[PDB]
Amino acid sequence: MPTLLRVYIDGPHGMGKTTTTQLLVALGSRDDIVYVPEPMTYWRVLGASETIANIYTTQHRLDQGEISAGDAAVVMTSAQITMGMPYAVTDAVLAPHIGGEAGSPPALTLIFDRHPIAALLCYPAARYLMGSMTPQAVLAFVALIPPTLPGTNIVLGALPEDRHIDRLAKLDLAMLAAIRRVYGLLANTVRYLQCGGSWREDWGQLSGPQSNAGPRPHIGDTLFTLFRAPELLAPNGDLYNVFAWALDVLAKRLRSMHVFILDYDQSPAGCRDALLQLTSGMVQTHVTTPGSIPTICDLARTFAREMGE
Amino acid sequence: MPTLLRVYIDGPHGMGKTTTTQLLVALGSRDDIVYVPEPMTYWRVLGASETIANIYTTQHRLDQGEISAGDAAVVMTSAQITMGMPYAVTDAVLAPHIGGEAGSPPALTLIFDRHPIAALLCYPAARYLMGSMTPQAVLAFVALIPPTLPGTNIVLGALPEDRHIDRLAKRQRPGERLDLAMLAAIRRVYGLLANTVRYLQCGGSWREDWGQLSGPRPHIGDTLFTLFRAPELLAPNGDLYNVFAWALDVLAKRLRSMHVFILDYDQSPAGCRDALLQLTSGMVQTHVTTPGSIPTICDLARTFAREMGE
Amino acid sequence: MPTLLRVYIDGPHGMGKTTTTQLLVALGSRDDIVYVPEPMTYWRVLGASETIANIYTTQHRLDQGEISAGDAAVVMTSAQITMGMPYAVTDAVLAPHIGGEAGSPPALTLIFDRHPIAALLCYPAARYLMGSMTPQAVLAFVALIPPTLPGTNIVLGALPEDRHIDRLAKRQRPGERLDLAMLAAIRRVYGLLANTVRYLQCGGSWREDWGQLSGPRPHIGDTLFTLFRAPELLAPNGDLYNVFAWALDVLAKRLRSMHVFILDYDQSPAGCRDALLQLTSGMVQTHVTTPGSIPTICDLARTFAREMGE
Amino acid sequence: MPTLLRVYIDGPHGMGKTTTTQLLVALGSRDDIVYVPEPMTYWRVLGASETIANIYTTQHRLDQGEISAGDAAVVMTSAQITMGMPYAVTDAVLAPHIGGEAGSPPALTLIFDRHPIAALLCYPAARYLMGSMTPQAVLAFVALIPPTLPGTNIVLGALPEDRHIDRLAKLDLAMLAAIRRVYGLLANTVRYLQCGGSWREDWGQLSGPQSNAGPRPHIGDTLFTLFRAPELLAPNGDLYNVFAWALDVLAKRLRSMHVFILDYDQSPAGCRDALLQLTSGMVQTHVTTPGSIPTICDLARTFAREMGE
Ligand SMILES: Cc1c(C[C@@]2(C)C(=O)NC(=O)N[C@H]2CO)[nH]c(=O)[nH]c1=O
Ligand SMILES: Cc1c(C[C@@]2(C)C(=O)NC(=O)N[C@H]2CO)[nH]c(=O)[nH]c1=O
Ligand SMILES: Cc1c(C[C@@]2(C)C(=O)NC(=O)N[C@H]2CO)[nH]c(=O)[nH]c1=O
Ligand SMILES: Cc1c(C[C@@]2(C)C(=O)NC(=O)N[C@H]2CO)[nH]c(=O)[nH]c1=O
């Protein structure tokens, strides 16, 4: 069978991800690499009207004291469903075509602009740090993350805050800090779990980044520490089982992924060549049937056409 | 490896004289049959404050013209995320323990109070019919329905509308409003769900029959697919956008492999208990992956009950 | 046009405490439910002399080595032509009156004692497992199964083997021999029938899975298709001849559209009566083609009963 | 949609049918006309061993007094199942591809060597006249005749008995008489039914050929008169309902067919040109889907390859 390489570029916005991906796609041939872009059309028109403007207005409202936290949470939560639709439906129809892992060329390389966890975990968690989402809602999205398909290669970004801020300024600094923290925690969470970390075993250590390198991080530097809020705990100090189960799901989903860090503090061509090198050691997978390749290509192109602008 | 029998009691609420959870308690006294009751504590306290009350209030305010359709949709979409949480979390931890089918008694019989599709498909669809949810939000929830595992036995109820209205009027839950439009909506969605599984099991191809909506198995007009002919999902030339067509493909794939059993609720609680148990004879059983899969499930069910069921 | 509900009681014989026809008589006292009983008169007199006796004698003689396998096959094939006649004739005159489906009470509920597949598929297949029929004759009968019309509801029974043996030992019919090998054979065929409908309704493609016989749905090894891997149907290179592959395509097409309901017979006649009626709630109903289709059916059933049922 | 022409050549053996059909097929192009031949391989090897030799031996046995009538009937009946298998399975898989009637060129013409009624009605009835089959068994086969697909054109043959006998002799004369009578009755039965004949209305007229031309025949000259045997009647003189229903099926199945008579008392080329002319006024049908034509061709060719020698 032919082999497939799926790469999800993710992490905080404004680091140079779209440019980098586009430069990568440009090097290859027409048919050996397809790009599933940002589904901006879905977020502005197809799924709802101006979902991103709606999200930023709500935050300002709450920040301003124009609305309550409960109201902000209802909006963010409802908006996140719209936000993650494209990522989720794409994963669901892609799923049946993915076979077992092969080994770190591929007949087809699929580069995605973000992964379902961006919408079902990362933004929700960042909004929770911003006060516009409750931890329970975050765990509700966590519980819906689809089973992690084999060969799930995720590329996160590293960019100095000053360089990031400098760049991002053509401005919610809090949201930028919250999103960077969440993605930093996410990288440690993968390492922690692949280094044999058990959140249940280390829960009590809570009180008061490298995704595939370095020593086992402390649970305090992973995503689990966001979920020790009073709302989730009982009168005895510990967390409720529903939420503890959500944490298990989180552990199961992140556990099998292969995450890589891409230094964006370089020129566009440098980033592209850094990403290229990073793809060498990524896990590829076989496809279920002979006709999977063509179908995956058509699926990606149709997504780009209909949803990416 | 031992065998497991999963039975999800579902359908429009308020059909039996006793609740699904009360019926469940009656059956969960054999040692070979454990239940996963309604997570009421989560809906009223844990996940948020009085979520069922919020839902019915919101619908009522929409109907009275006090709030906009978009305002209701935001509340209802967010409310459904909270409502399905326990089901989604239950499915995800139980999934790895479910093996392949066995054939046509089982070591353990797990009986649930609803399946993830009620909070991810059925309730949202009903709210779409009530004007309180967008069809795009409904397909977004459909896109997140967990893969259908082997041995997914779903019991839906049969009950004449007037008897349903009557029986529902006697158990008005905390914050619930007796709404005949919603009862019609929810009963229709479940009837369409039943027809859809049949349609799909009999060869039905939604893409091939789509044209029949605008001009042996049920007609596509009598399945859940008719609901998604909504104008919000169509491009200027009337074609369904591909995003939504993919959600329908997912819907088709998730439903087709489910085994639907119809329970006649027009009888007494005792009768509904016998009936249900009789129905188990034609249900599909699966094998469990590990030797210690029985106990994990039992504890899951016990812990769930203890914590979320009162 | 009024609606009709057809219910075919089938499965391995000797499961309920009362016969299928006796149960039928009990239900045929409402004016909205007519029955088509067992055509015993045809089998013992009309069509030929004591056909059931001939069958069991023949099997017994085969087992004792008094007659050849080919001699038994000739008798058994001819005997099955006679056994299914009434069912085939019933289907063909009733067919033109059956219209398309209605949806998920009916004007008339027609309850039959067996469906053409028992005499055209199930019994012959069992006899193939008993060495008294060739697999080619079984596929020849399968090739003549009338097209499956809409609303084909088939009730099959569930009953633990020892209880089945016990209950069957108390009603030994005229000329019948209590054969445990045949009971195993017939019970297996019906279990495989049930699995086959499921297999097919869930996506199953016999041609695509055929390779698995020699090296979510039931494995093809647990469906009726495994029976036809018999060496008599294969060419020198192991491929199934096309004649037979076409018979399997027909089998696939006839079964897939049937709706199977499992009835637990491990209870009393009264219980089996309630159960059956409860089961009607999830059965598929159809419309009739003409306004005078109700009466024709009633008279058919009445005339049938009167003449062939004692 | 493309149109299809199905023609079933049938009638008594030895009239010049195979030759005629072969000459017909020869005139057309490769792909516009396919021939579904006699499935001799199935009858001699695939379905059973020497089914025809077995049938002729049994008749001789009974004629000789070596076996009883009951024994002969069990054999003939069992043999007929084998005999009609190929015709029946072919009709069953062909069925889904046949659309509604069009009008008396076609994209594809299918010429069959016999129709299911040969095995499910005609031979059984002829064996009943020969005493080797019971009338009840005959009606059991009649009850299994598949629904008559639209565009069912059947061509029967006409040949003087002396010419037929002369020809057939390189010898069961009784069987030849019985088969000719049965096919003669069959032609009248179609005419009778298409002229508004009702067997139930005329049953009492019993006591003591043109298929698409002439006046309404008397029931006494149709197939219904074979079924007034004592075995089928009750003590009150009339027939039993089971059998009466079988007669209805017979009436329903034959009613919609379009039967033609082909004079075989001519030279091979004459027969071919007579058959050609006869196909001009035959009913064609549409096919359900675009790909039906190719599939029907493959089905016919595969039948010819595997079953016709
Ligand atoms: C993915 C995602 C984003 C991220 C997006 C949608 C956002 O903020 N703005 C935009 O221009 N594109 C992306 C940034 O790369 N934002 C959000 O609120 N929820 C989400 O789920
Ligand atoms: C499952 C479900 C219900 C069903 C529930 C939560 C309902 O409304 N009221 C109640 O107290 N318990 C159940 C009835 O079976 N309702 C709803 O709005 N969305 C859902 O997703
Ligand atoms: C239907 C059927 C039966 C079933 C019957 C005829 C059986 O064997 N004995 C009896 O007296 N009535 C039925 C039992 O339900 N048996 C058989 O050999 N071939 C068939 O085709
Ligand atoms: C079709 C048929 C025949 C007819 C056939 C099979 C026969 O007799 N001999 C043979 O050489 N080919 C045919 C004659 O055209 N004979 C029979 O006994 N039963 C049947 O059903």
Image (spheres, coloured by chain):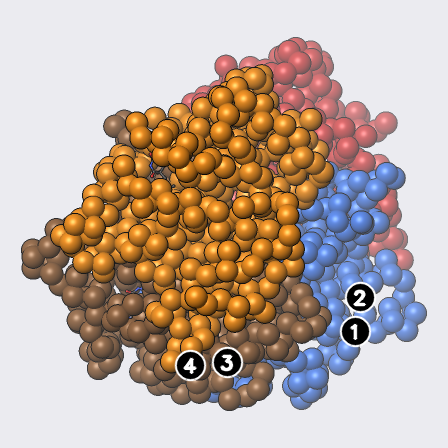
Chain colours: A red, B blue, C brown, D orange
Q: The disc labelled 3 sits on which kind of residue?
A: Arg
Spatial separation of the CA atoms under disc 3 and disc 4: 19 Å
Ligand 1 sits in quadrant = top right
| Disc number lying in front (4 or 2) | 4
Image point (25%, 28%), residue name: C236
User: Marks 4 and 2: CB-CB under 8 Å?
Assistant: no
- Are the residues under marks 4 and 2 on the same chain? no
Are there few (<14), some (14-19), or many (20+) residues within 10 Å of tag 2? Answer: some
> Which residue is the site of mark 1?
B181
Check the residue under mark 2 and report the chain it is in.
B
> Which residue is the site of mark 4?
D236
> Which residue is the site of mark 2?
B130
Check the residue under mark 1 and report the chain it is in.
B
Q: The disc labelled 2 sits on which kind of residue?
A: Met
Image quadrant holding the C terminus of chain B, namely bottom right
Are there few (<14), some (14-19), or many (20+) residues within 10 Å of tag 1? Answer: few
Q: Quick one: label 1 or label 2, which is nearer the N terminus?
A: 2
Check the residue under mark 4 and report the chain it is in.
D
Spatial separation of the CA atoms under disc 4 and disc 2: 67 Å
Point out residue A249 in the picture as x, y percentages from the top left corner: 51, 50
Would residue D265 be visible to someone looking at this image? Answer: yes
Label 3, ligand 3: CB separation under 8 Å: no
Point out residue B43 in the picture as x, y percentages from the top left corner: 64, 70
Q: The disc labelled 4 sits on which kind of residue?
A: Asn
Spatial separation of the CA atoms under disc 1 and disc 4: 63 Å
Q: What element carries label 4?
A: loop
Image point (55%, 38%), residue name: D261
